[PDB]
Amino acid sequence: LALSLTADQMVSALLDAEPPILYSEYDPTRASMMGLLTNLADRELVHMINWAKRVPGFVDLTLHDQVHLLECAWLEILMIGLVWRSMEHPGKLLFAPNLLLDRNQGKCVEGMVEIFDMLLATSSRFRMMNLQGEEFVCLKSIILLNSGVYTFLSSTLKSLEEKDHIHRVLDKITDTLIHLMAKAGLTLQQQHQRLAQLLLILSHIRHMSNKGMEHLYSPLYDLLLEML
Amino acid sequence: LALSLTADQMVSALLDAEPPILYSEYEASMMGLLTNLADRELVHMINWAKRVPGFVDLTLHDQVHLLECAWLEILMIGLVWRSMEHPGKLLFAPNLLLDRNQGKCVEGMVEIFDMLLATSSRFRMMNLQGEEFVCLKSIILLNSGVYTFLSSTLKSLEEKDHIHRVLDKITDTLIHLMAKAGLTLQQQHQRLAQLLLILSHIRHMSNKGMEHLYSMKPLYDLLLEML
Ligand SMILES: C[C@H](CCc1ccc(O)cc1)NC(=O)Cc1c(-c2ccccc2)[nH]c2ccccc12
Ligand SMILES: C[C@H](CCc1ccc(O)cc1)NC(=O)Cc1c(-c2ccccc2)[nH]c2ccccc12
């Protein structure tokens, strides 16, 4: 089980579990921004479930506890995926390697500009700190398990042994980061400061998710069930 | 300045800045009972913000964006912190203790209630000490709307760059607190994480609340006159 894995081990199996590069699908003999979003979000979804299930401990869960998470964390895992490949492309959003975008395109829809700009903003942010792929996967994980921990169902008995399992996985993923930046050669002080700005950027991505939701909402449960 | 303070020094001036406990103002309604009480808590927050080590160095535009972004978040963690010895209940004011059913008559408060109630339990379980709390409340002040000002012009660059160093300062403040406490450094690293990851749930709750607070449709005219 996950709760024996190592820093060394956790990273690797996390890199292992990475989804595949997905290429957009637009008229080459030429368009909508919406459908361009819908299309590939769908497909980015299907491979989430296949990565999620590869996250250590996510399986140890429950099908109900696994469906709540993903139903809460989905837009955030996309965003931090996007923002990661968008780093060497300042001012542009690298959805797919054949679908780099920028501001003016997000303005075509109805509220995408603000989300673009926060998106671009986190990209710059991560750019500044020089985010390693090894921390990125940690943080995609931490976005997964932290999604809807504190809103499962009830304070029952099982609910509690569950919550107790994630909180230990998360704790385990944390030593991974700390240990990653340790290897890197940072003084302990810089480990604690680095880890915090990283864990503070998660508030921003959550905030964009809710932001994003409000127009995506302006079924999914029944879908994750079949896939999970 | 804040970037000269020590842990004990930062704690002190943070403990120092702590606002006063407010009692509610009372067929009674939850809204006006709620509305009434935040306002007056807002007025004390503004005077608490102005006492946060480093917030002053910023700009009236960088000071008015922050507060205007993270207000609901400072209240919520402030409520959720006193609501800790009150399992299932939200201690708004010492005379306005509530629960789900108290929030149920208003049209959406239960969901915010429940998640509100859950963070309290979380804080309880981890045994959140006031000195880590005052720190986290500051961290929500500084993290508020950092990456969302407008432009990275000349001052914005030096400003955001200063914020990130205040926060870097608070960050070590907490560690020494848990360190002093005698945790393995590993235990310091987990706690700081379980702690800072809870700030997304407060943020997530704030965004929810906003959705409803503008479901009932100012601040600027206040922060400007009070700052
Ligand atoms: C810009 C982000 C999209 C993040 C994203 C989308 C697809 C992908 O492959 C990778 C990353 N969108 C939102 O935050 C909200 C959103 C809107 C949206 C925003 C504003 C107004 C209307 C619709 N349409 C969709 C469609 C699919 C996912 C998210 C979203
Ligand atoms: C339950 C939470 C916390 C509100 C709150 C108010 C005062 C205070 O000192 C601490 C916390 N409410 C909100 O986040 C949003 C909100 C609503 C609200 C939300 C949903 C439906 C109706 C009303 N009414 C008010 C009034 C004053 C401040 C915030 C709020």
Image (cartoon, coloured by chain):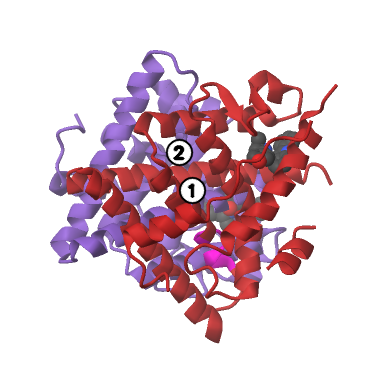
Chain colours: A purple, B red
- Mark 2 is surrounded, within 10 Å at the Cα level, by few (under 14), some (14 to 19) or many (20 or more) other residues, namely many
**Magenta residues (range):** B142-148
Q: Which mark is residue A147?
A: 2
**Mark pair 2, 1: CA separation:** 9 Å
Q: Chain of mark 2?
A: A
Q: Which residue is mark 1?
A: A76
Mark 2 or mark 1: whose residue is earlier in sequence: 1
In this view, the residue in front, A147 or B98, is B98
Residue depicted at 33% across the width and 48% down the height: B192
Q: Are marks 2 and 1 in contact (CB under 8 Å)?
A: yes
Q: Amino acid at mark 2?
A: Ser
Tag 2 secondary structure: loop
Q: Nearer the viewer, residue A81 or A98?
A: A81
Nearest to the eye among marks 2 and 1: give it: 2
Residue A202 is labelled as none
Specify whether residue A137 is in view.
no
Task: Please tell me whether residue A43 is drawn above or below residue B33 in the rendered image.
Answer: below
Expressed as whole percent of the image width and height from the top left, the position of residue A200 reads 42, 55
| Vertical position of residue B76 compared to residue B227: above or below | above
Which amino acid does the dot numbered 1 rest on? Glu
Could you tell me if residue B126 is visible in this image? Answer: yes
- Label 1: few (<14), some (14–19) or many (≥20) C-alpha neighbours in 10 Å: many
Q: Name the residue at 32% across, 69% down.
A: A130
Q: Position of residue B223 (x, y in %)?
A: 71, 64
Residue A156 highlighted magenta (yes or no): no
Regarding mark 1 in the picture, which secondary structure is present there? helix
Q: Identify which residue is drawn at 63% across, 52% down.
A: B71
Side of B104 where A14 appears, left or right: left
Task: Using the rendered view, name the quadrant where residue A84 is placed.
Answer: bottom left
Most extreme residue toward the top is A157
Q: Position of residue A100 (x, y in %)?
A: 50, 68
Would you say B84 lies left or right of A145 here? right
